Image 1 (cartoon, rainbow over the protein chains, first blue to last red):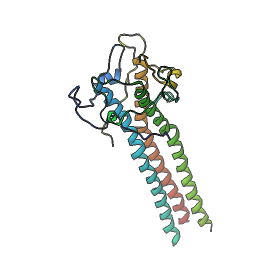
Image 2 (image 1 turned 135 degrees about the horizontal axis):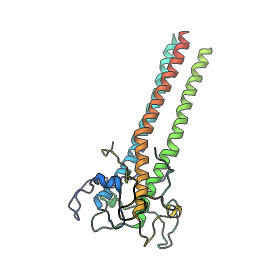
Image 3 (image 1 turned 90 degrees about the vertical axis):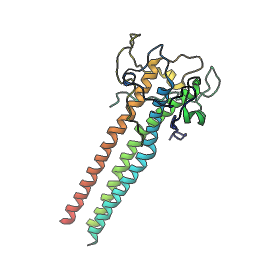
Image 4 (image 1 turned 180 degrees about the horizontal axis):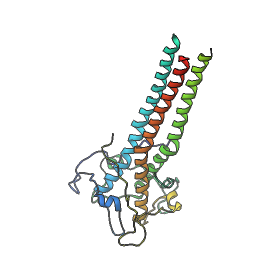
Amino acid sequence: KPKDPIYVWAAADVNLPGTGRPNKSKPIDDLLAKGYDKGQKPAAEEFNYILNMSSAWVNWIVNEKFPELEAEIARLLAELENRINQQLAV
Amino acid sequence: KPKDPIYVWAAADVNLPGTGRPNKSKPIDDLLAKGYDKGQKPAAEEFNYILNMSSAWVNWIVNEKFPELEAEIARLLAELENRINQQLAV
Amino acid sequence: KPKDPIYVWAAADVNLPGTGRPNKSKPIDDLLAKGYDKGQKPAAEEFNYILNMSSAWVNWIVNEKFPELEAEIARLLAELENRINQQLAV
């Protein structure tokens, strides 16, 4: 419904001149459980990684899982109807 | 399961008092491809837009897609049963 | 499919080490409808809360809601097939 195609944040993986490191790095699990506090300022890698997570997975849900699922349910119904059709034919 | 309803971030589409410009804007594609670096700094518009997109798509998945998919699933089976039972009665 | 095994951000619910307040808090709807404006100072509370909401709602859908729907589809199809099989056997 929303009028903008889902854009995956930091889709590409590359080195940044500022850091020299990959654009995305996994936050340490301590931070994942805890989060930030006043005074902390995020590192770019963790920010990019989190946004890429939350965008790529929504993209997957919308464009891969569902288009698969409607097709699968339709095919299931069609095959059940077909089987009952051979059963009736006799 | 999550315990609270899913609110949208920056739901409204209005000119901010501080800026006088729309509260949301698409980040430039180049920035999406790589994300922020050490020196680069976030703008308010992009920051709001990312979260708004995430929350809106989460709404569209949860409160819209599954209910209508379930309704379609029920309807398909009902129509198939009706079609079969017509012939069976015949 | 995404390679990331999604994780819940700020999954732990405890007061901040440097501040007695909780690590998460729902932003006032006033801000939710508008979004951060120029010169505002984001607080870790709201960022953590929104990330928690997004991550939890993503993983719930990914890991629970889809298997449930698939199981329901399978059971419905099996039972529907069985009904007509029995009736045609009669």
